[PDB]
Image: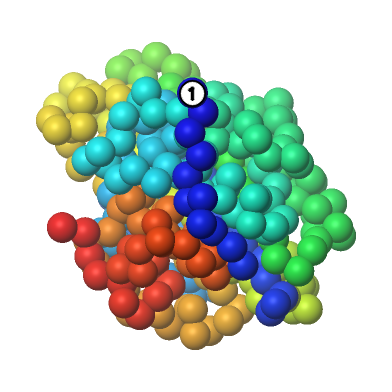
């Protein structure tokens, strides 16, 4: 059975939301949030982006996180067996222009399947996403959501995620055989991947400022965190309930040229939020009218409260 959701949904202003779904990035290594060893957020710091310092993920592996964050279900009631429409289907059926560009080696895990304009790239440098993004910026409609799904910090071959121009933190760990590396070198490599992702964000913002015929927003969040040898744990996917915050505590970053959203975002940044919030935030952004919309979960809505 393929269940439909928000069957009562419907929708003016010229709007553009760029949703960036990250990969393996963990909040603890964001300088936007007070990480001091390496300045990982050098680029988006210059755009005064809003950083959510208390943002959690739905799961500890892509297979749970990616579908769940886009699903109507929150972490406590999500099941992997559910097979139904997600936030993107609701925006599409409600007439919003939806594009999904995927550079992630794992795919969209079924989220993008029913979109008309979706693309899979080769999972090389994330910068390749800027190509179909620029091309979609020519054929915009009145309301658009563009999803960019990053390879981001995918491990264990971290050193392959960024070009030499962003090997800024050294020495590095240029192997998948992570336990052989000094831990500082491993961290440096991991931080470089964050830096590269940070740069790409500000390049997205940079293209967004050339589009002022529209109200433009960037929302970036990771699917989950990552362990880097602390307590002998590597990679991710540890069962959520026993997982270290390294795997569940993720970055979330918002930017808009509409600085009223920018200041609603700034007001919420310290609240206990999570991927649970993505569903209503995405409906709310394109003003989708429906009963499944929960105003107290929309990040860009004054009635937003923290998670229970
Ligand atoms: Zn993942």
Identity of the residue furthest to the front in this view:
8
157 in relation to 210, above or below: above
Does the rendering let one see residue 68? yes
Count of number-bearing discs: 1
Q: Which of 259 and 1 is in front in this view?
A: 1
| Residue sitting at x 21%, y 25% | 239
Q: Which of 167 and 289 is in front in this view?
A: 289
User: To which quarter of the image does residue 271 belong?
Assistant: bottom left
Q: Nearer the viewer, residue 1 or 49?
A: 1
2 in relation to 117, above or below: above
| Quarter of the image where the C terminus is located | bottom left
Q: Where is residue 64 in the image (x, y as percent from the top left)?
A: 37, 30
Does the rendering let one see residue 199? no
220 in relation to 264, above or below: above
| Residue sitting at x 43%, y 53% | 279
User: To which quarter of the image does residue 206 belong?
Assistant: bottom right
Q: Position of residue 14 (x, y in %)?
A: 72, 75
Name the residue carrying label 1. Answer: 1
In the image, 153: left or right of 162?
left
Q: Which of 89 and 269 is in front in this view?
A: 89
255 in relation to 283, above or below: below
Q: Where is residue 289 in the image (x, y as percent from the top left)?
A: 51, 67
| Residue sitting at x 51%, y 57% | 8
């Amino acid at each position: 059975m393929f269940k439909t959701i928000a069957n009562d949904a419907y929708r003016h202003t010229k709007k553009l939301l760029v949703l960036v779904v990250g990969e393996t990035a963990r909040a603890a290594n964001y300088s936007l949030g007070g990480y001091t060893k390496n300045d990982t957020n050098f680029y988006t710091k210059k755009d005064n982006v809003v950083f959510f310092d208390n943002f959690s993920s739905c799961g500890t592996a892509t297979a749970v996180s990616l579908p769940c964050m886009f699903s109507i279900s929150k972490r406590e009631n999500y099941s992997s067996s559910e097979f139904q429409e997600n936030a993107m289907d609701v925006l599409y059926k409600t007439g919003v222009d939806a594009a999904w560009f995927d550079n992630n080696s794992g795919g969209c895990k079924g989220v993008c399947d029913r979109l008309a304009y979706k693309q899979k790239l080769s999972s090389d440098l994330d910068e390749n996403l800027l190509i179909p993004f620029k091309e979609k910026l020519n054929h915009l409609s009145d309301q658009n959501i563009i999803v960019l799904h990053l390879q981001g910090s995918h491990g264990p071959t971290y050193y392959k995620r960024y070009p030499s121009e962003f090997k800024k933190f050294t020495p590095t760990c240029d192997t998948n055989e992570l336990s052989k590396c000094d831990s500082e070198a491993l961290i440096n490599t991991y931080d470089n991947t964050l830096l590269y992702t940070d740069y790409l964000l500000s390049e997205i913002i940079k293209l967004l400022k050339e589009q002022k015929s529209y109200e433009s927003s960037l929302f970036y969040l990771s699917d989950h965190g990552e362990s880097l040898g602390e307590n002998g744990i590597y990679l991710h996917g540890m069962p959520y309930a026993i997982a270290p915050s390294y795997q569940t505590h993720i970055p979330a970053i918002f930017w808009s040229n509409d600085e009223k959203l920018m200041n609603l975002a700034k007001e919420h940044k310290g609240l206990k939020l999570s991927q649970d919030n993505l569903f209503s935030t995405l409906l709310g952004y394109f003003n989708v009218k429906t009963s499944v919309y929960e105003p107290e979960y929309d990040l860009l809505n004054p009635k937003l409260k923290a998670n229970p």
